[PDB]
């Protein structure tokens, strides 16, 4: 039994070196790992070439189901284990088994011996030789003798640590058993006071991690760039001490300090650190001191994860949740008869090389990322509750030959069982299992993770679609009306009129929803209760809300007013719009209260416009007179300037016209008091010299839309679709739940990817006949056999407008790489 610190493959093929903790101190020993690959060679009879020394066997493993691979054909799969040295020597010639006729690909050729050893063998290494000296003077061979023991406790750790840090010339070093700090080219006093301050502020953490790392140290602020080599050598002969690395140039530091390859090291890369251009000393001091005093908690968490997941310390990292998923899932498949499709240094599933080719169905499943939603505008007098839906993907996964696009059923079942056992373990107070459950969805979406298949992602998305529509149907089974739908928010119209009466109703409804077997794992929370709502859009609504219904007391009612349409008004009319919106909301509240006091038309709201008709008309007349008087004055030209915003496309002249048009369209949403609104609108339009059904008196959307789907937040794992045009500022740059700023070059890259996928989709479109909508089925042909000329499924003007709005968006904010992307066209 031995605890492995690190695995590492040698330059010679099939040879690996390990820093292991021998019964005394650490020790290094050499191994030999053969390779294992899977072929599809010939149909039933093959040129075996048995004279070559290797192991061959016709297996019956489960191959991945590619959409393009529709013909099973010959299925005599072969399992070949083979040392990599002879593989490299036989790669030279062509007359060999690897390259012949009827060779259909290699399925497990990109798996290093390091990976095979760390998945099958693990850190808990032991021997059962029962020639140990002869096996340690040379590399101990493992394929004949290998096994993994239990790993409940990895090791009782009591041994020194190292520390080398960099902040873009801020190379820093520290020793646990040292007593000095020197920094490469007021500071000392600030350093001492800050260290003492965070000492008392983290006394408890320091005490509870002192057994890992333990004190004032000498400070120094140091032709000087060669001292890294000297310090590394000095620490090499001073101790045998794990190294902690923190810099954006880890590979550069490893390649420029030759001594760093001689000891096991643990990397803690948290890059993207920048300088404030002024007073960088306090912030850098804070960074270094918090890193120094949090390394103990870091190593505690790392040893927890390692001794939980049977992974060596040096091969772990704080944010490598996907790696553990890959390791566990891969070993669970290895004990199974399923080929791993393992991939390295490429975000594509391994399929034998077929995956390099371009195929239409793969292209369409790659770019199918948009998610639908439900919006039913109108004015509601019934109470409406706002709920949130959580843990949707996990419940969707856990709940539930002919089709070539289907994902493999066996892998789906295995993943469901693994997720179920993780859920059960996390229920029994396991933080690691909880973190794994939280990170599962991010692992699924992220292509950078290995064992990633777009087919599986599409399968999950399709299942989520079906589950959401089923949930909507279930909510519709009882008395309910869905106002808005999304992956995160659902608004439901309640039959009753008083919020106080919906307490037991809402609780019973949510209880019944939870008790449903397919909705067992969902998490439902109620946020707000609505008294009177004017809902037309996600970004444009106003109403009266109470947070939560209390007992024996009248609830607190607050008014909300979110209207992007207000921004597109003239600067001088926005106060008028606000005031009149407030007045009309007050009138509707008053008439609903009066009707309720009395006891597809509803007398709750009918007759509400009689309260404010004449003052509104007089005010509109006064506004028209003043605008007529002072429109051509130069000093008054400032307040009549129509603002320009991203996504604006309408070109119009008279501001009062849009003011009244919006003020009438907001009222027209009644869907039950149409005639009164129409009479009022005609009377308003009579003030101008216009007519009831004129084109210029028609309201439109004063903005376009540009939505980015499946936007992810690293800190909170929140998934939402962000709109680059309709959304207000100071929300594009920060996550909704957690108030953490977003990275900007990520936004630019995502916009560029969306644009390029759009262009590709336009360029790969199909052709449809004009008269009969049948599709083109021939490569060369002038027209349909019937009458009619071909037209494209994707019209040109649509993509032209899309590019226009990309241009406007990129111009509004600072987006330079996107501008360069435009320029290359
Ligand atoms: Zn977030
Ligand atoms: Zn036709």
Image (cartoon, rainbow, N blue to C red):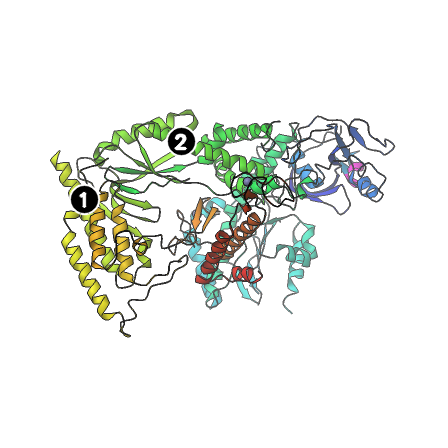
Q: Position of residue 13 (x, y in %)?
A: 77, 43
Quarter of the figure with the N terminus: top right
Outermost residue to the front: 787
Q: Which residue is mark 2?
A: 471
Q: Which residue is mark 1?
A: 589
Q: Specify few, some or many for label 2: CA neighbours under 10 Å numbering under 14, 14-19, or 20 or more.
A: some
Give the structural element (helix, strand or loop) at label 1: helix
Give the structural element (helix, strand or loop) at label 2: helix
Q: Give the left or right position of residue 192, taking residue 141 as reference.
A: left
**Does 326 lie within the magenta span?**
no
Q: Nearer the viewer, residue 294 or 271?
A: 271
User: Does the residue at mark 2 contact the one at mark 1 (Cβ under 8 Å)?
Assistant: no
Q: Give the left or right position of residue 615, taking residue 386 as reference.
A: left
**Where, by quadrant of the figure, is residue 335 drawn?**
top right
Quarter of the figure with the C terminus: bottom right
Q: Position of residue 451 (x, y in %)?
A: 61, 38
Q: Is residue 4 visible?
A: yes
Q: Which residues are magenta?
A: 133-139
**Does 136 lie within the magenta span?**
yes
Q: Nearer the viewer, residue 632 or 354?
A: 632
Q: Which residue: 38% across, 56% down?
A: 729
Question: How many numbered badges does the structure rendering display?
Answer: 2
């Amino acid at each position: 039994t031995w605890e492995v610190l690190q695995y590492k493959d040698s330059g010679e093929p099939g040879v690996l070196e390990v820093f292991v903790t021998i019964n005394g101190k650490v020790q290094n020993i050499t191994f030999h790992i053969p390779k294992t690959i899977y072929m599809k060679f010939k149909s039933q009879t093959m040129p075996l070439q048995k004279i070559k020394n290797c192991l061959i066997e016709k297996s019956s493993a489960s191959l991945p189901n590619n959409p393009k691979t529709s013909n099973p054909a010959g299925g005599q799969l072969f399992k070949i284990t083979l040392p990599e040295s002879v593989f490299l020597e036989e790669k030279e010639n062509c007359t060999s088994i690897f390259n012949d006729e009827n060779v259909l690909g290699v399925f497990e050729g990109t798996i290093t011996p390091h990976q095979r050893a760390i998945m099958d063998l693990g850190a808990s290494v032991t021997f059962r030789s029962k020639a140990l000296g002869k096996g340690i003077q040379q590399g101990f061979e493992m394929k004949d003798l290998s096994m993994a023991e239990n790993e409940r406790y990895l090791s009782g750790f009591s041994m020194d640590i190292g520390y080398l840090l960099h902040f873009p010339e801020f190379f820093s070093l520290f020793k646990s058993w040292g007593d000095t700090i020197t920094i490469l080219v007021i500071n000392a006093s600030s350093l001492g006071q800050i260290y003492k301050q965070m000492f008392e502020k983290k006394k408890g953490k320091i005490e509870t991690y002192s057994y890992l790392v333990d004190i004032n140290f000498e400070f120094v602020y140091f032709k000087l760039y060669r001292r890294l080599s000297q310090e590394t050598t000095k620490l090499k002969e001073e101790r045998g001490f794990l190294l902690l690395l923190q810099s954006p140039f880890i590979t550069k530091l490893l390649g420029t300090i030759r001594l760093l390859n001689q000891m096991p090291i643990v990397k803690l890369s948290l890059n993207e650190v920048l300088l404030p251009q002024l007073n960088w000393q306090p912030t850098l001091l804070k960074k270094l001191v918090n890193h120094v005093l949090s390394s103990g908690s870091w190593i505690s968490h790392l040893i927890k994860l390692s001794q939980y997941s049977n992974i060596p310390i040096c091969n772990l990292r704080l944010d490598s949740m996907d790696y553990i998923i890959d390791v566990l899932y891969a070993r669970k498949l290895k004990k199974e008869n399923i080929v791993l499709w393992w991939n390295e240094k490429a975000p594509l599933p391994d399929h034998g090389g077929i995956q390099n080719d371009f195929d239409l169905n793969t292209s369409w499943i790659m770019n199918d990322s948009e998610f639908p939603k439900i919006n039913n505008s109108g004015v509601y007098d019934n109470v409406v509750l706002d709920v949130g839906v959580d843990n949707l993907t996990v419940n969707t996964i856990l709940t539930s030959e002919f089709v070539h696009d289907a994902f493999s059923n066996d892998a789906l079942n295995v993943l469901r069982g693994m997720l179920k056992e993780w859920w059960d373990e996390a229920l029994k107070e396991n933080s690691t299992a909880d973190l794994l459950v939280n990170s599962l969805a991010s692992w699924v979406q992220n292509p950078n993770a290995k064992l990633f298949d777009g087919l599986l992602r599409y399968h999950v998305h399709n299942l989520t679609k079906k589950a959401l529509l089923q949930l909507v149907n279930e909510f519709s089974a009882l008395g309910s009306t869905i106002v808005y739908a999304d992956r995160n928010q659902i608004l439901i119209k309640t039959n009753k009129y008083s919020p106080e009466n919906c307490y037991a109703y809402s609780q019973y409804m949510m209880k019944a929803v939870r008790t449903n077997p397919m909705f067992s794992y969902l998490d439902l929370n109620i946020k707000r209760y609505w008294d009177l709502l004017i809902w037309m859009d996600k970004f444009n609504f106003s109403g009266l809300a109470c947070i939560e219904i209390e007992e024996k007391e009248n609830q607190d009612y607050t008014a909300v007013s979110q209207w992007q349409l207000k921004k597109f008004l003239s600067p001088i009319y926005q106060p008028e719009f606000e005031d009149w919106m407030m007045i009309i909301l007050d009138s509707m509240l008053k008439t609903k209260q009066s009707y309720l006091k009395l006891n597809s038309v509803e007398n709750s709201l009918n007759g509400f416009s009689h309260l404010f008709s004449k003052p509104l008309m007089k005010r509109v007349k006064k506004l028209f007179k003043n605008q007529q008087e002072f429109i051509l004055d130069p000093q008054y030209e400032a307040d009549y300037v129509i603002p320009v915003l991203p996504g604006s496309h309408l070109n119009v002249k008279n501001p009062l016209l849009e003011l009244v048009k919006s003020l009438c369209h907001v009222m027209l949403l009644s869907k039950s008091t149409i005639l009164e609104i129409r009479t009022l609108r005609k009377e308003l339009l009579k003030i101008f010299e216009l007519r009831e059904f004129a084109k210029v008196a028609e309201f439109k959307d004063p903005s376009l839309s540009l939505v980015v789907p499946d936007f992810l937040c690293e800190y909170c794992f929140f998934i939402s679709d962000i709109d680059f045009c309709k959304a207000a500022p100071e929300s594009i740059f920060s996550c909704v739940r957690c108030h953490k700023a977003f990275n900007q070059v990520l936004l630019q890259e995502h916009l560029i990817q969306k644009l390029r996928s759009d262009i590709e989709s336009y360029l790969i479109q199909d052709l449809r006949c004009s008269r009969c909508h049948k599709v083109k089925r021939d490569y060369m042909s002038a027209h349909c056999p019937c009458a009619g000329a071909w037209e494209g499924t994707l019209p040109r003007e649509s993509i032209v407008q899309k590019l226009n709005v990309f241009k406007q968006v990129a111009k509004y904010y600072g987006f330079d790489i996107l501008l360069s992307c435009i320029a290359d066209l």
